[PDB]
Image (spheres, coloured by chain):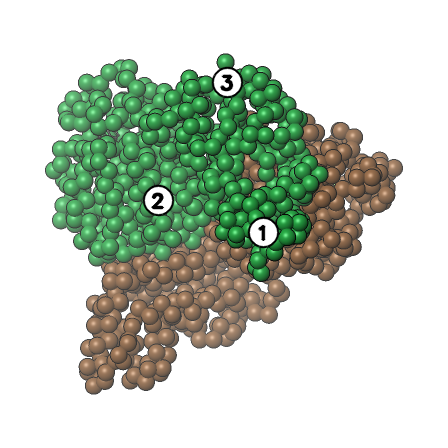
Chain colours: A brown, B green
């Protein structure tokens, strides 16, 4: 029975094959057929290309040897290479044109999800070209999804030599009959076949994937749209910044490029952005996913006033100061969404661009108490239940697994009576002790939130709602301002509290505001509709956040 | 007696004054004298500029009000503003031309070093211009050097109103007679003077600094060249990445831009780069200063093989993978310098550029054992003392303060007999029990290293020298390669072990190698000559690392 799948890089996980450019160049330049492919393989196991693939020499040392071989081949075929012939140019274009073969990666991802050990086995080179970063980027994106990456130039062995196959089996800790090996070169399949491995000659991806599903008995073709890549907490870079004597802020960091600071809502974590972090980093951004003050590995002081917007915003500015960041793009959800609008209003010089999921920008009404304003809308009643210190903490901390399983549910799975919370005596009075697992989350994802909330509980997080008068007084100072920096408002059709219509007047205060809208999306936006959140955010980032 | 110094921003800590552009524009456009300055102050305390400075409105809301005032003033003076007159253009140019007044900052730095509480008190605005980042950058660089930053637009008060002065005194927790107040506007000095504060009207910096030194009794003018800004460990962003089950890597992070990964030597810390971190971040780079494997907050497994170059390099690649970085510039010193050359040789696709301080690149000699090669040079004898597990650990761990005070000394303070270590029975046999403090370090800086080494000791750090045969075998695989990516070699005149002449053949293997050289520099390069290290690295980064 199969328990391992091995994939080649060129012509299998990455298309078009770099090899096939030797043929295309021949046709474009009207050179004798196979001339470039002949000079490429010249000398066979003793040749320049084999030395390159074994790591004896670098790609830049190989370029003049290939040119020298191209001349000798043309001299024999009684032909002349054009005025401006360049192996460097040919390969630079070929390498940058090569992209990930998405359905092949999807199949490898699906096999690994079903318990398979996966690996990339490739005949490759040590790339020291001025433009080597393009290929470094491709290898980084691909390799993360596999258990092993075996590169000929690092191991000093090359396919079709029998030793590399014995090396692969030792790395996999598997018998050859347990292995599927996919390659676009028949000669390179041959030793794997002769050893007893199942082999697939890859020409078109579709036929290769049909052969792959028939032999594994796992559906890989025509399968539903996969979720974006998530985060394994133990594999992330974890950062810690002391913003003041008793306050440290924790964040997870991924990628290079303009800093994108992600600000979760209540009662969440950096992990609420798990489906956005790999996507935004891959789109060319340096993601900083916060544990907001009161949460996870960040400090959680008990004082209510430690959680007013003025204090929270000041601390986020210090967070940027200590990291040496002059600016960051601020993206928030729920309470994080409220914080990001006030970062834009009070510190525009520090905010590259601002985006909010669900949370509209509504200015303070200076002729009405915030307590009065909130009583007007019956959907905001649950926030009055949060006012009395200790009441909501006791119910939310009682059973953590029940708390998160009850809260994190899609719009058509809701188990909560949001009205009338105070009167009913609690959020979960008509809710089960053992809620069923929502289709949005796994048991393990719930257990991550449970473990995070074991440290500081719900006091600090609930304190965010306990500064309505302080926040109102501070917000009134901004009543003559407008938000004029790049801004995005993302509405969720089925958020029954932060309703899309509440954002309707925003253009009066943010004239150049851009919008996104997600149909059939509840309150837990990032995990409810991750693919669409990523599409909207990446599109807005590339256009407005530089 | 004075214990606090307060500085204005425009015309005092930053020059040329943004105000003075109103006058220059008048002269350039041949407009009536004081016309632009009149429309700027139009309406006085009730005017548009006062509302701006109090934070009632943003800079972009103010621009059309200023234009409207400029028209009314021109209509009265019976003049016509030119075809293409733009307040936006005038102020964009004025703000970007304004730079830090270096000698004024140096004086504030010197006063704070002598126990003074320092603050910036400024009449400023909420900047929402498309080009606001330039000013955000300036405020970030300046503010870090002061105890307090009081901005009119954040406090809703403005100079010369008496309330802002009472607010300043409350923030300083000082009586007015204890305060020196420096301002370029006479009207703004007046309430501070009337309260009993010492006031300096700032026209030219030199005269202002003479007045400042006469009143404080502290030399501020003609004082020696200051050291670059250092790091306070508790104020840095601390990052943590698990590279494998038993191995976590710690780093300090500062700045935005291309990632620059700093790799210390033996027996050091991320803190050895304390004078480079703020400088490189200010030059436009994202600095990642490592605690290398075996050190500080990074894991220190006991096995010798955990510290061979192959393992260390692989882990540094995983470190980049987990952070989502496709590349980084690698800068190393001593053992870190050796690691960076092999990162360039084995992983060029992941290395944006490579630089080494003191450590030359010398290829493996495949016809000689590394143990033989090292015996040939008597300066490398101390490395043989490091071979036997437990011997060097015992002497180095015996008295940590003695260890670091003995090691970290300039070329003309050396206390160590580097020959013949093994024969003499130790590094510190002819060294004092209580070494005098080197001119390069403070007691507090030594105590930081002492506290760091209390965690894991010297086993992991010494293990870096215990893989000579393993490293030699791995290095021989690279003998046919060349380093062709951007590279910098920095030599230290007085490093008696890693001598400048040892780097002489490097061009044979790195043909496009760039060089730097530091005269009168010992082995502890970063702390011995910080200003010159920063100049060489910043110059090479801006030219070759993009
Ligand atoms: C799902 C539902 C109704 C919706 O449609 N919008 C919101 C907003 C907040 C909460 C919420 C958050 C925390 C908590 F403890 C209780 C309820 C729940 C919801
Ligand atoms: C200062 C001096 C001689 C010099 O000029 N070059 C070097 C290189 C290494 C060490 C050193 C490092 C660690 C240790 F434990 C002992 C000596 C000491 C030196």
Residue B520: quadrant of the picture:
top left
Residue B409, given in percent of the width and then of the height, sits at 26, 25
Q: Which of pointers 3 and 1 lies earlier in the amino acid sequence?
A: 3
Residue B427, given in percent of the width and then of the height, sits at 22, 24
Q: Residue at x 43, y 31 (%)?
A: B205
Residue B112, given in percent of the width and then of the height, sits at 46, 24
Q: Which label is found at residue B538?
A: 2
Q: Residue at x 53, y 49 (%)?
A: B26
Q: Which residue is mark 1?
A: B87
Residue B197, given in percent of the width and then of the height, sits at 56, 20
Residue A388: quadrant of the picture:
top right
Q: In this rendered view, identify the residue nearer to me: A494 or A14.
A: A494
Is residue A344 at all visible to an observer of this figure?
no
Specify the farthest residue to the right: A423
Chain identity of mark 2 = B
Q: Which residue is mark 3?
A: B3
Left or right: residue B163 versus residue B214 is right
Structural distance between the alpha carbons of marks 1 and 2: 36 Å
Q: Which of pointers 2 and 3 lies earlier in the amino acid sequence?
A: 3
Chain identity of mark 3 = B
In the image, residue B454 sits, relative to residue A337, either above or below, namely above
In the image, residue B36 sits, relative to residue A308, either above or below, namely below
Q: Quadrant of ligand 2?
A: top left
């Amino acid at each position: 029975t199969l328990r391992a799948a091995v994939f080649d890089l060129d012509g299998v996980l990455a298309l078009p094959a770099v090899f096939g450019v030797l043929g295309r160049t021949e046709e474009a330049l009207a050179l004798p057929r196979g001339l470039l492919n002949d000079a490429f393989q010249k000398g066979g196991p003793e040749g320049a290309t084999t030395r390159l693939m074994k790591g004896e020499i670098t790609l830049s040392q190989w370029i003049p040897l290939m040119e020298e071989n191209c001349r000798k081949c043309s001299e024999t075929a009684k032909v002349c290479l054009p005025k401006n012939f360049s192996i460097k140019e040919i390969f630079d274009k070929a390498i940058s044109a090569r992209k990930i073969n998405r359905p092949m990666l999807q199949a490898a991802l699906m096999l690994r999800k079903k318990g398979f050990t996966t690996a990339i086995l490739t005949n490759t080179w040590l790339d020291d070209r001025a433009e080597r970063d393009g290929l470094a980027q491709l290898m980084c994106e691909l390799k993360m999804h596999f258990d092993f990456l075996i590169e000929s130039c690092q191991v000093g062995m090359v396919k079709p030599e029998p030793q590399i196959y014995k090396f692969l089996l030792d790395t996999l800790k598997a018998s050859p009959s347990e292995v599927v090996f996919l390659d676009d070169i028949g000669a390179n399949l041959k030793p794997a076949r002769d050893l007893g491995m199942v082999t697939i000659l890859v020409q078109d991806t579709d036929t290769a994937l049909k052969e792959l599903e028939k032999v594994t008995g796992i559906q890989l073709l025509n399968t539903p749209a996969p979720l974006p890549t998530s985060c394994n907490p133990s594999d992330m870079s974890h950062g810690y910044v002391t913003v003041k004597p008793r306050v440290r802020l924790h964040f997870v960091e991924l990628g290079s490029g303009p800093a994108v600071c992600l600000c979760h809502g209540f009662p969440e974590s950096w992990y609420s952005w798990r489906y956005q972090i790999p996507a935004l980093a891959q789109a060319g951004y340096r993601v900083l996913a916060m544990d907001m003050k009161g949460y996870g590995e960040s400090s959680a002081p008990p004082e209510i006033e430690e959680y007013c917007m003025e204090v929270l915003c000041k601390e986020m500015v210090t967070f940027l100061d200590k990291l040496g960041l002059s600016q960051a793009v601020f993206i928030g959800h729920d309470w994080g969404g409220m914080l990001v609008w006030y970062m834009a209003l009070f510190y525009p010089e520090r905010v590259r661009a601002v985006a909010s999921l669900n949370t509209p920008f509504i200015p303070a009404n200076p002729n009405m108490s915030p307590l009065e304003s909130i009583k007007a809308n019956p959907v905001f009643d649950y926030q009055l239940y949060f006012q009395e210190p200790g009441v909501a903490e006791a119910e939310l901390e009682q059973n953590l697994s029940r708390t998160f399983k009850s809260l994190f549910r899609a719009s058509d799975e809701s188990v909560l009576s949001m009205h009338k919370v105070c009167e009913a005596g609690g959020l979960f009075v008509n809710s089960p002790e053992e809620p069923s697992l929502s289709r949005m989350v796994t048991e393990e994802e719930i257990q991550f939130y449970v473990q995070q909330f074991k440290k500081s509980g719900f006091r600090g997080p609930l304190n965010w709602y306990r500064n309505m008068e302080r926040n109102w007084k501070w917000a009134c100072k901004s009543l003559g301002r407008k938000i004029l920096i790049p801004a995005l408002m993302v509405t969720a059709e089925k958020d029954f509290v932060l309703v899309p219509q509440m954002s309707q007047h925003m253009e009066d205060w943010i004239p150049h505001l851009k919008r996104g809208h997600i149909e059939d999306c509840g309150h837990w936006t990032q995990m409810d509709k991750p693919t669409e959140v990523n599409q909207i955010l990446i599109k807005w980032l590339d256009s407005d956040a530089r």
